[PDB]
């Protein structure tokens, strides 16, 4: 099975920093998108950031300039370097893999989620 | 043979109408299936459905009876509807290849680049092209051969053979089949090349610690990518290859084989639901519909 | 044994008036390809009992019948169905090739 192991979150002071890491153990097609989505308390899950195998990247407006989604060139692991944090960034952050191996459609994988809480 | 041949044509129409009805139903009925790509799948399914309802059934009769029972007007109009729908099927297959190529290789660019409205224009283009390759030349008699023996079929309402001039046969076959086939090969080959170049970058990235090998996902992707080009080519290459052959030396390939290869192309329209609608949302929808 | 050995006179009774399928074989002693299918027609006479009856007409001894159906080369296997020619095949062929011809034309 393909499984996504999330780490690097927790409590942190405002104006601070964290470094999320999602290691995807299992068979993934070479062409894919590893990303981070987040679900704020009583809100809909939104994209935070995402990085293609190619290396193109897409960030949500809120976290532009602050966060940096990079991936391990070797393994199937993706890192969201979160800097200059604010209390609005507090959410459950979910790792995601869009796998393009079927070609016509894409198959999704979601991590359990990991809590990030930014106090003022 | 002729008892088995007649029975074989029947389930071909059944498979075509069933599959494509099921697809359109699934897409229309499920909010989750109404994606950008499935918009192009909807165009395809419409084309193949009309093939199964009107095109193939009249084609079944003409083989079984040995003659056209519905006069010169409907011969032309059926022939025009046949060419139109086959053109639209094959060209929409080609659009989907492009759509998936961009959705896989350049996913973020593609989202801004391809809107729903832009896709609608693309669909309308394909049907407009299909119309202008089919109805316009066929109904205005631009296809016609000068030959007296060919002109005996045009005068006979019982004869509904599609004998064309050199120019139509080449241009129409290129536009409707060969150009789409090349585009599909080119496009889907960049998908192969993109994936293989990406596997190369992982081996370098390791600092000479691991060498990647084809996993489960890669073998399936290459099988899938094979089925697409395989079934499409198997189904229409024979008919369209022979279609150009008869422009030079008409006697070389017999009439029965020419028609046998056209039934193979009609078979494509049944296969397309199977190839292009395997997504888990499709599978869920299909079970919910049944 | 089970093959009808035709003549010009008895062709109307043995083929044109005959009930069901008749597989006529126009052949000659001088034709090498004609004798190549001769043993295969013996096996086909057994294996298609009820479905068809094999008939043979030697065109040297019976020259009058062959011109009427336009026999150009030999051997020519004309399959008659109730006094009417349905299918045609000219030249020598193996057992499997003749079975494919007969099974297709009989159903
Ligand atoms: C004679 C057959 C003519 C059929 C014409 C149907 C066009 C199909 C249009 C379609 O499927 N759309 C997506 C919805 C709208 C563009
Ligand atoms: C042989 C058949 C091969 C397939 C035919 C499909 C090509 C259709 C081309 C097409 O529709 N566009 C060019 C895409 O390359 C779209 C653009 O022209 C786009 O700008 C417009 O849709 C609107 O945005 C204008 O407001
Ligand atoms: C991307 C859009 C490209 C479409 C246009 C280029 C290909 C089709 C153009 C074309 O018409 N032909 C070249 C295709 O090979 C064939 C005909 O010109 C030719 O068959 C006859 O006109 C002559 O035989 C007259 O005696
Ligand atoms: C919205 C996009 C508008 C573009 C639509 C243009 C379609 C391509 C032009 C065309 O129709 N043909 C090539 C022009 O030759 C194919 C045939 O119609 C033509 O070749 C035959 O009618 C003649 O060969 C008959 O002698
Ligand atoms: C894990 C194993 C994965 C299997 C990979 C199989 C690919 C085989 C299918 C295939 O590639 N072709 C279908 C041929 O039937 C050839 C086409 O790519 C293309 O060459 C033709 O469509 C035309 O160029 C012919 O003119
Ligand atoms: C029995 C008939 C003739 C109705 N079948 C047509 C076939 O299903 C589809 O054939 C074609 C599709 C697109 C373009 C074509 C074409 C045949 C030719 C020609 N020249 N140009
Ligand atoms: Na006619």
Image (tube, coloured by chain):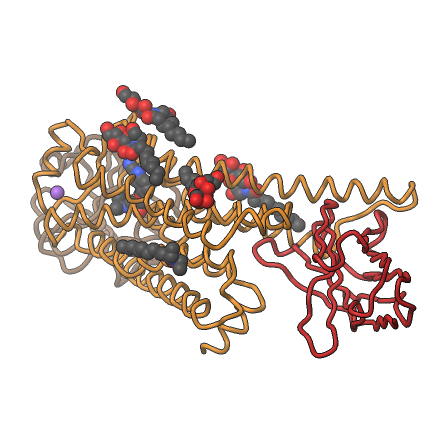
Chain colours: A red, B orange, C brown
In the image, B247 versus A61, the foreground residue is A61
Q: Position of residue A61 (x, y in %)?
A: 70, 57
The residue drawn where x is 35% and y is 64% is B17
Q: Residue furthest front?
A: A120
Q: Quadrant of residue B154?
A: top left
A49 on left or right of B261: right
On the question of residue B182 being in view, the answer is: yes
Q: Is residue B284 shown above or below C82?
A: below
In the image, C87 versus B230, the foreground residue is B230
Q: Position of residue B156 (x, y in %)?
A: 8, 42
B161 on left or right of B238: left
The residue drawn where x is 20% and y is 42% is B161
B144 on left or right of B83: left
Q: Is residue B136 shown above or below A68?
A: above
B276 on left or right of B254: right
Q: Position of residue A38 (x, y in %)?
A: 74, 68
View quadrant of ligand 6 = top left
The residue drawn where x is 9% and y is 46% is B157
On the question of residue B243 being in view, the answer is: no
In the image, B107 versus C30, the foreground residue is B107
């Amino acid at each position: 099975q393909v499984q996504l192991q999330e780490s690097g979150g927790g409590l942190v002071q405002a104006g601070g920093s964290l470094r999320l890491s999602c290691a995807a153990s299992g068979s993934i097609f070479a062409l894919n998108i590893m990303g981070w989505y987040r679900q704020a308390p009583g809100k809909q899950r939104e994209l935070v950031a995402a990085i293609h195998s190619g290396g193109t990247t897409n960030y949500a407006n809120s976290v532009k300039g602050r966060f940096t989604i990079s991936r391990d060139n070797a393994a199937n692991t993706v890192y969201l370097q979160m800097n200059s944090l604010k209390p609005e960034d507090t959410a459950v952050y979910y790792c995601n893999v869009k796998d393009f191996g079927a070609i016509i459609y894409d198959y999704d994988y979601w991590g359990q989620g990991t809590q990030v809480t930014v106090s003022s | 043979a002729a008892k088995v041949m007649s029975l074989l044509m029947a389930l071909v129409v059944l498979l075509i109408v069933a599959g494509n009805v099921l697809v359109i139903a699934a897409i229309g009925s499920t909010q989750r299936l109404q994606t950008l790509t499935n918009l192009f799948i909807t165009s395809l399914a419409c084309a193949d459905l009309v093939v199964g309802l009107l095109v193939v059934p009249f084609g079944a009769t003409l083989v079984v009876r040995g003659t056209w029972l519905w006069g010169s007007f409907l011969c032309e109009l059926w022939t025009s509807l046949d060419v139109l729908c086959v053109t639209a099927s094959i060209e929409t297959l080609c659009v989907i290849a492009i759509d998936r190529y961009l959705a896989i290789t350049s996913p973020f660019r593609y989202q801004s680049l391809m809107t729903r409205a832009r896709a609608k224009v693309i669909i309308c283009t394909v049907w407009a092209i299909s119309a202008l390759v089919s109805f316009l030349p066929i109904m205005m008699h631009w296809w016609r051969d000068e030959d007296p023996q060919a002109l005996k079929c045009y005068q006979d309402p019982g004869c509904c053979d599609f004998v064309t001039n050199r120019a139509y046969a080449i241009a129409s076959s290129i536009i409707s089949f060969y150009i789409p086939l090349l585009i599909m090969i080119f496009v889907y080959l960049r998908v192969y090349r993109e994936a293989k170049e990406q596997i190369r970058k992982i081996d370098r990235a390791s600092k000479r610690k691991t060498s990647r090998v084809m996993a489960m996902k890669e073998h399936k992707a290459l099988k899938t990518l094979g089925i697409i080009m395989g079934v499409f080519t198997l189904c229409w290459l024979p008919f369209f290859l022979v279609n150009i052959v008869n422009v030079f030396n008409r006697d070389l390939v017999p009439d029965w084989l020419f028609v046998a290869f056209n039934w193979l192309g009609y078979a494509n329209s049944a296969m397309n639901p199977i190839i292009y609608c395997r997504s888990p949302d499709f599978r869920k929808a299909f079970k919910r519909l049944l | 044994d089970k093959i009808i050995h035709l003549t010009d006179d008895s062709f109307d009774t043995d083929v044109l008036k005959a009930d069901g399928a008749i597989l006529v074989d126009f052949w000659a002693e001088w034709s090498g390809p004609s004798k190549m299918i001769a043993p295969i027609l013996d096996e086909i006479a057994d294996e298609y009992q009820g479905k068809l009856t094999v008939a043979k007409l030697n065109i040297d001894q019976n020259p009058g019948t062959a011109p009427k159906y336009g026999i150009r080369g030999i051997p020519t296997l004309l399959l008659f169905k109730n006094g009417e020619v349905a299918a045609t095949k000219v030249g020598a062929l193996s057992k499997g090739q003749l079975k494919e011809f007969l099974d297709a034309n009989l159903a």
